[PDB]
Length: 177
Length: 168
Ligand code: CLA
Ligand SMILES: C/C(C=C=C1C(C)(C)C[C@H](O)C[C@@]1(C)O)=C/C=C/C(C)=C/C=C/C=C(C)/C=C/C=C(/C=C/[C@@]12O[C@]1(C)C[C@@H](O)CC2(C)C)CO
Ligand SMILES: CC(/C=C/C=C(C)/C=C/[C@@]12O[C@]1(C)C[C@@H](O)CC2(C)C)=C\C=C\C=C(C)\C=C\C=C(C)\C=C\[C@@]12O[C@]1(C)C[C@@H](O)CC2(C)C
Image (cartoon, each protein chain N blue to C red):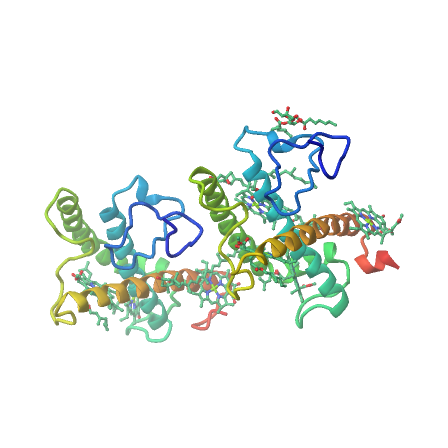
């Protein structure tokens, strides 16, 4: 009856055990929202998209700062400020990436709403397993848990890197030391 | 359910299997409120127009017709051809063809039996049975889509950088 994460709180009604990373940590009861097209399905899809985006962004920042930029690309070690140097010399790359992300996000929203309507697609599912790393069950749950935990950690990390780069105008590991 | 192209999206519910080049790609559901034959005709018309346009752009940046008016790049050829009246002739004959097309598409939508884009233009055969016709229709659709995207890229690159045939 009590949430596993917060023993002083009752179990959130909509979070039983199903989703990976579920420990009952919903103090504000946001999982019970059923308005403005927002429900547990939409919240989970948003959480998974945030997890994946944060993982990609944190990996990119760390890669560029440690191993350096790719040939022909600007340096500076400040990832929040090197973006304007890339846009100053290769605006077409940024524009094409933005257009591609826009199209993919329109497709993602359509897929999310459709799967919410005629329930056949789990939240965050895009059938993207080209290498077959999660075919069999009893490993899919473990992979989902790993992805969720890594994505939450990378969300926090990427938000921290964004704020550090905006404020200190220095690199992430530069702030570290 | 679970359209072939986008495996996580539902089938567009208007494209089951009985159209050439039908991989179930309609995420925004254009076929849900527009006739399928109308959209097919529009797509095939775009394919043919853009194939001709890409070939003409690339060729005219290499080979020029005799005369001083034909000595401009394809990027600047529009303002020269419109002034000389060269594009007026193309406009006149294209308008004639498109009025006949108005009649044809109206008849196709109101029964008839004319397949979308089927003008029966076939001096040579190149398509003897149903299988050959289907294969060549798929080839035409794929080549036309590729040429539409290719002309888009060619025009955008040439406008961005006023370069010759290599528009990099
Ligand atoms: C979308 C189709 C299209 C359009 C609008 C244009 C437009 C133009 N072309 Mg052009 N061209 C095209 C296709 C096209 N071309 C193709 C496919 C080729 C390859 C043979 C060429 C080869 C070409 C050359 C070599 C030159 C031009 C030039 C020009 C410019 C002025 C003279 C002229 O009209 O061309 C004259 C066109 C030709 C001599 C060949 C056209 C052959 C046609 C397109 C193929 C048969 C299709 C058939 C007749 C369709 C019937 C239509 C129906 C309604 C009845 C003008 C901007 C001239 C210029 O100023 O260059 C900058 C020039 O020197 N074009
Ligand atoms: C209606 C809609 C879409 C939809 C739909 C459909 C289509 C109807 C389908 C469904 O049926 C429903 C629904 C709702 O899904 C809404 C669209 C979404 C919006 C409104 C898009 C918002 C995106 C904004 C982002 C993601 C911007 C991020 C900015 C960053 C800046 C980066 C910086 O580097 C910059 C530039 C400068 C640097 O110095 C430092 C920083 C600041 C870090 C980080 O990235
Ligand atoms: C949109 C795009 C790029 C957009 C870039 C933009 C907006 C950038 C704009 C800017 O930089 C400028 C210009 C100047 C700056 O000052 C301002 C900004 C704004 C910064 C590229 C698309 C590029 C699109 C591309 C490359 C498409 C390739 C498509 C292929 C290969 C298709 C293949 C098929 O069609 C066939 C062949 C057969 C079919 O049946 C099957 C498939 C597979 C679908």
